[PDB]
Amino acid sequence: GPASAAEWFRQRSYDYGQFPPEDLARRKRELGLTVSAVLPSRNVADTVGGIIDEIHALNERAPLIDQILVVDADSEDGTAGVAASHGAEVYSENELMSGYGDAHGKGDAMWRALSVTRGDLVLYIDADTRDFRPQLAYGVLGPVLEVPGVRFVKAAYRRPEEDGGGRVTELTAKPLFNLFYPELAGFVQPLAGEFVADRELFCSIPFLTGYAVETGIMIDVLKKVGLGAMAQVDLGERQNRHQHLRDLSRMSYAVVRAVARRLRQEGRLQQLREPGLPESFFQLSDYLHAVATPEGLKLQEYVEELVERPPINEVLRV
Amino acid sequence: LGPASAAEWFRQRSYDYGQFPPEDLARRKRELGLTVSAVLPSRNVADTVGGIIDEIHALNERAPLIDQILVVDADSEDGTAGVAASHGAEVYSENELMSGYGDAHGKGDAMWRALSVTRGDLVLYIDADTRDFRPQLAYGVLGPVLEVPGVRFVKAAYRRPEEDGGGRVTELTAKPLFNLFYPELAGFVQPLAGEFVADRELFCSIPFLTGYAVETGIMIDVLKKVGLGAMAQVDLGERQNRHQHLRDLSRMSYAVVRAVARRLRQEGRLQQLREPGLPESFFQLSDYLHAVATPEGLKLQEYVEELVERPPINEVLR
Ligand SMILES: [Cl-]
Ligand SMILES: [Cl-]
Ligand SMILES: [Cl-]
Ligand SMILES: [Cl-]
Ligand SMILES: [Mg+2]
Ligand SMILES: [Mg+2]
């Protein structure tokens, strides 16, 4: 395995420039591999159309993506119809793994998607990217297709200069990973939605359902394949999204919850509830967010249960 | 028995500074014979400490509340010392106080050492970098210590100029971490606030973490010492934001994480932190690894900060 974070960073970081699309396509045909691109799509009517159009144009020059799969996460904006009218295979998430109830977020979408992905490789992609450059499709395929032993590949990129990622990455994930999962500290965008692996890998791990999904995947893939089999590819620039700091806070909470849950399974965290601490203070699903408003201080409460899906292998018709 | 919930505490222990007219506070302070020291941990703040001291003096004219003003200077290159002295504050070098401990390890070291020169029954910590120092920044948090019996420790609450739950580190690191591991603290609007007051005995009876981890350690240790019902916060109105770079915030977030981790390890909630099989080269809590994307490629950068716990100053000074 890798000797240190730094040795991994050196051996397992690439630029998209090292994998021209033509070459990859040649290689893929040679390997006899297929690729499903999965777009978990929640109210992305203004963007999925463009992404699908670009994947299509890419496939013109170099056939790399076999299945374009949009999973509509109960959108109210016309997402499903936009995706459909641009030629993607579209599924509502309610209709997949239907015995599971209704959509419980990005993770649930990404997980359920596996039941209809046909490719040997599953490439997850963010559906909300505003100017989708071809390399957001193929860049991460580079190392899975060409480097022995590499099994999982994450995007790295920068906003429009030293980009350590968005705010949840910078202030929640990187700090927690440095402390608890030092092997993950070399990833530039550990929470990126573009990543690819063998379909079998994804079918064999649990998926956290909400925002914590990328966090749980990073940790579980690490434990499964080892750091040496993980890589990242510099894809250049990505206009980061805008969001309200107030809403990032609950996303940060999910990241925390995911680490805490994994720490508890490893046995590093035990007796999470402090003996002495009254029951009334203890409710993990209950997030309190104290704020100051022009009208006084207020205690806001958010209730989100941390739902987790089992390895879909265990639960899908074989 | 204490508050039965964070919401119960939030109602009973949150105040507005309007509830504590300074002249009323001054009377009660006089009646009890209490003195107050104001401690300003100062690193390169020549442009702001002048006003702060000035304003504190102006407030004492209407209502004597601060008996001693201590500027503890981190050997600023900007003439902080001269400014503060000429404005009539007492000035001390952080490296001269408690010098047997060597040179100072950042903000927390300076705050701890100051306890060797504060003579006040009560110690009020204040930010030295505030641009517009309003009167209530000097008296607001004194309200409950003085007027509410049972209350020993009071934290500032405030908003930036619809719903302010704090700066990025507070929002994305502290609140998430406290919600999970220290739910008793989730009602604090500004848990990492630099301005807060307690009795000197209390401060002398707890360790201080050095560096940026100090505010976190204090919250957790005060909580354990006196209980939630003895803590309060007071809304102080509008506080200007001092904005900084998302990169540098990452190191600060990591200090919050480190402070929580250490307390968890000491309680026994966290154990066997270094996973077995993880090569020694990966495990170094003082080394923060910060992966970034630059226009010249991906870069793994590294920040080193030794975390030091100063003992309760009572154990040093008999
Ligand atoms: Cl859990
Ligand atoms: Cl839950
Ligand atoms: Cl430690
Ligand atoms: Cl250390
Ligand atoms: Mg809770
Ligand atoms: Mg380290």
Image (cartoon, coloured by chain):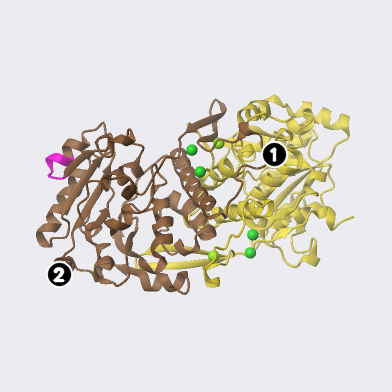
Chain colours: A brown, B yellow
Question: Closer to the N terminus: mark 1 or mark 2?
Answer: 2
| Residue B182: x %, y % from top left | 62, 42
Magenta-tinted stretch: A83-88
Residue A161 visible, this orientation: no
B272 is higher (above) or lower (below) than A79: below
Hey, which residue is sitting farthest front in the picture? A318
Q: Is residue B300 left or right of residue B25?
A: left
Q: Is residue B300 above or below residue A179?
A: below
**Tag 2: amino acid:** Glu
Which residue corresponds to mark 2?
A30
Which percent across, then down, holds residue B137?
67, 37
Dividing the picture into quadrants, the one containing residue B132 is top right
- Residue A130 rendering spot, x and y as whole percentages: 25, 47
For the residues labelled 1 and 2, the Cα–Cα distance comes to 63 Å
Q: Secondary structure at mark 2?
A: helix
Label number found at residue A276:
1
- Quadrant (top left/top right/bottom left/bottom right) for the C terminus of chain B: bottom right
> Which kind of residue does numbered mark 1 sit on?
Gly
Circle 1 marks a residue in which chain? A
Q: Tell me whether marks 1 and 2 sit on the same chain.
A: yes
Point 67% across, 43% down: residue: B195
Side of B227 where B284 appears, left or right: left
Looking at the image, which residue sits at the far left?
Answer: A60
Taking depth in this image into account, of B72 and B146 the one nearest to the observer is B146
Q: Is residue A115 magenta?
A: no
- Some atom of ligand 6 lies within 8 Å of the CB belonging to the residue at label 2: no
Q: Does residue B295 show up?
A: yes
Give the quadrant of residue B66: top right
Look at the numbered disc 1 and give the secondary structure of its residue. loop
- Front position in the image: A268 or A90: A268
Write the residue at 37% across / 67% down.
B298
